[PDB]
Amino acid sequence: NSNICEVCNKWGRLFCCDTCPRSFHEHCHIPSVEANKNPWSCIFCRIKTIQERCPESQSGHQESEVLMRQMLPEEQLKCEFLLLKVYCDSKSCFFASEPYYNREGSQGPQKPMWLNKVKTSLNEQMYTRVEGFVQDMRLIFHNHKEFYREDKFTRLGIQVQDIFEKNFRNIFAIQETS
Ligand SMILES: [Zn+2]
Ligand SMILES: [Zn+2]
Ligand SMILES: [Zn+2]
Image 1 (cartoon, protein in one colour):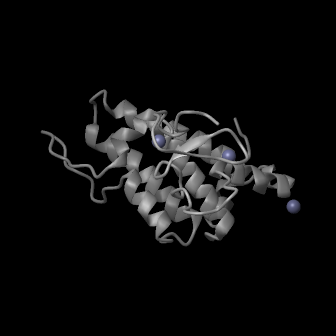
Image 2 (cartoon, protein in one colour):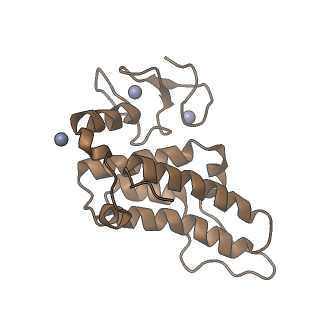
Image 3 (cartoon, rainbow, N blue to C red):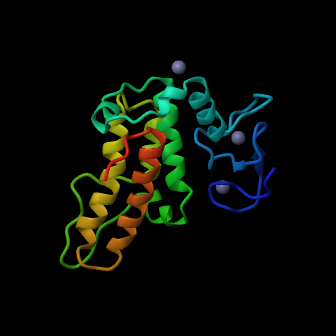
């Protein structure tokens, strides 16, 4: 197994996957690494299993159909994995915890949103459709772009949104387009 967390790239108290060489901090894995379970399989491995069981699941889909899906166990897992892929980028730090807004010439968003809030909402089964999760994720970056206006720091929202969107297309097998 790797000697660093797959998500934050630090050593520490690491749990090792039994079916692949990845390792995790307890609360870096999503869901949080399970108490017992021998053997244990990481989220990467669980996602690969879904694909292998249903190879047609990789055929292209329309985004509108994906968003309307109910959050049954496989869609729950896919959203947890997508969230974890965002935390894998170091730039997620800017979006992880609760923000506050006090900048001359800007007003804070009407509906603040952050990654740890989406993480809690997934854990608490607060989303009934994929659309709820995706809307809160896109709201993070939209709030950031609107608040930071012409400051170059706006770019951090474009960067981490691009990681979200590429992973969304991959994980939910969105039909490739020009
Ligand atoms: Zn970690
Ligand atoms: Zn694994
Ligand atoms: Zn099948």
